[PDB]
Length: 106
Length: 106
Ligand SMILES: Cc1ccc2[nH]cc(C[C@H](N)C(=O)O)c2c1
Ligand SMILES: Cc1ccc2[nH]cc(C[C@H](N)C(=O)O)c2c1
Ligand SMILES: Cc1ccc2[nH]cc(C[C@H](N)C(=O)O)c2c1
Ligand SMILES: Cc1ccc2[nH]cc(C[C@H](N)C(=O)O)c2c1
Ligand SMILES: Cc1ccc2[nH]cc(C[C@H](N)C(=O)O)c2c1
Ligand SMILES: Cc1ccc2[nH]cc(C[C@H](N)C(=O)O)c2c1
Ligand SMILES: Cc1ccc2[nH]cc(C[C@H](N)C(=O)O)c2c1
Image (cartoon, rainbow over the protein chains, first blue to last red):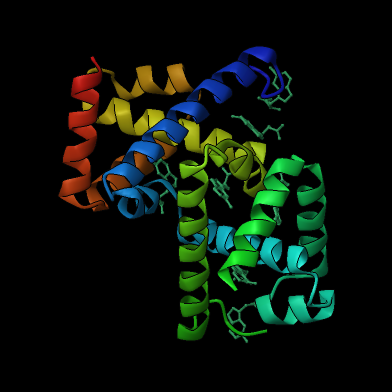
């Protein structure tokens, strides 16, 4: 098989990913997102995404310490730091939107 | 830490997952789904979801052989069979919706 690092494989994985994104958009529009995501993801993957969202929310809120976050979520420090790095790599427009969504939800 | 198999951890992972699902719904509504998903997933995870969607589409279409599907997607037979099993475990309403979405897209 080909290298996973080739441009060709990058293009293939990029186009297939966007097909998934569009199918999930349509599932949300028809209220089928939950069964689609149970089809397309494993339990561990859904668990990881739940953990990651809580890490994002608590890092942006700034109220909990890393120690408290580790205990509350059962996620190690390395995972929390990867989440902080991932936030910093994301566009400012997304980070600000997330902050605003959280602010209003209080 | 607690067992990953306890009811308590199942409930925690279930509630955190649903928080992710709702945040992603809101991202789609604001056209921020692509940056949110780049934040929340790795490249390999996006690659896997693209591969899985193509497996679903080609299994439902029934036109390609498993051999052809393996070659086209660079996914082994074990992954294709896991996809077939995953389809069969999913609700009929979802499987039929996917078939109908594909039919119309032709
Ligand atoms: C053709 C090729 C050349 C370079 C490569 N770097 C990684 C891989 C994937 C895996 N190691 C394999 O051997 O398939 C690979 C493949
Ligand atoms: C089929 C394919 C496509 C994506 C992949 N991500 C990691 C791998 C394994 C590879 N041997 C490596 O670790 O570089 C790999 C292979
Ligand atoms: C959190 C998450 C989200 C969705 C995912 N799809 C695949 C994976 C990991 C898997 N072992 C792979 O990379 O093929 C994964 C993980
Ligand atoms: C919030 C958070 C917490 C831990 C995480 N582990 C992997 C990811 C995905 C990230 N976009 C990446 O490619 O590493 C991630 C995100
Ligand atoms: C408390 C407890 C009891 C039963 C368990 N089955 C799996 C685990 C997780 C891991 N093996 C660990 O040792 O944390 C675990 C933990
Ligand atoms: C933190 C936590 C929560 C979810 C998990 N899925 C797998 C594991 C590893 C564990 N030792 C096992 O393989 O049963 C694990 C642990
Ligand atoms: C279409 C397809 C192809 C291969 C796959 N590997 C893992 C999954 C997710 C599935 N819901 C599960 O829990 O195994 C999956 C889905």
